[PDB]
Image 1 (cartoon, protein in one colour):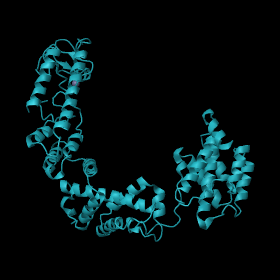
Image 2 (image 1 turned 45 degrees about the vertical axis):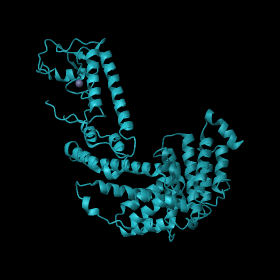
Image 3 (image 1 turned 60 degrees about the vertical axis):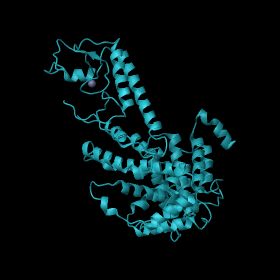
Image 4 (image 1 turned 90 degrees about the vertical axis):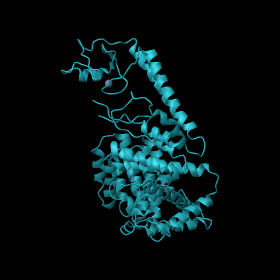
Length: 490
Ligand SMILES: [Zn+2]
């Protein structure tokens, strides 16, 4: 309190000495002014505020109620601007010093500070009702002359308050939550605030676990014990408003547990047996997933699995009898076929490769080949990128046909003659380089499909990247691509 009053009256005296006894911002916007205008009552208001408020029949002062004689004509471009800049520099220095002081002195060790200090820290953030919007939130400003015209919630105070153990900081954050939901965030999208809180708690628990000196087995034992003794207690904080801190801690803990579990599942998929102890953790995860029906946890698990590894990971993971099926719901496995196809990632260009690839697919299933020509003739992005899309569509169609065993060697079933006639007729790709590339591609003699990769997972991605960079080089008549062309082809 003593140092806070020292900072406050130091700022007051500094401003008084700097700019002639008390520069004050605009009373309407309550923030630092742009293009300052000086009233006869030694008042500084914003140009926009004064132009939007002094136009009607209220030629007076919102602060001290003094009549304005003529107009807001006198503006000071010499003293007010420099004084405002100096006071802003001092206020930013004070804010940075205050945040550094609270970060260092208030959390030196594992002992929390007193109570009134935390209460004043969480109470100074507001600009509570003044006679005139009301009750804005600040970016840790010990002063009252800085606001924003929107209630904004940060997380620096919350994060710095979660550094200690969660057992002794629940009431303070609970009071802060009740304040925010009672005064600024009564009825709105509370999902954003809930996810902000849960992410802050994930960060805090990650800091606590990583910074500590403990082996992984102790944490695994505690996690398994919690999983095996977790009473649901879900219905307590569900319906519309109630969200206890304990519930948030529990869901954060299960988030961390399933994050690690997905990491371990990916590691098992890319590796050998799991040392007979990680298997117990995965079995506990499976029993937890099959015991509770809150399928959001498995949704998050598969989302994290896709983020770490990719869509192809779950695509191969969703087969028909692999001993890892508990990560799917009872409905996804029910109506999923064995004909899951690869992904047409070349849609980056936008609404042009899709049409040509659909035309190529229709020409593949049928015998007519005029559809791809019609699709090519009805689009922008001329000849270079046009032929790029055409040949990429042909490659992806032939790859989809070959990789799937049911329709292997499909073009050889009276369809390669159609594509050969299409190449012969249309002159859009009747260039020797494109012609020989297509001749290699159609009969699958290109030396890229036979990558002989034992993993057979990323080999499709590798071939896709190789053929895509080859297409970019072939269709790119650019000076920057000449060395790459020479490296790839000569
Ligand atoms: Zn203003």
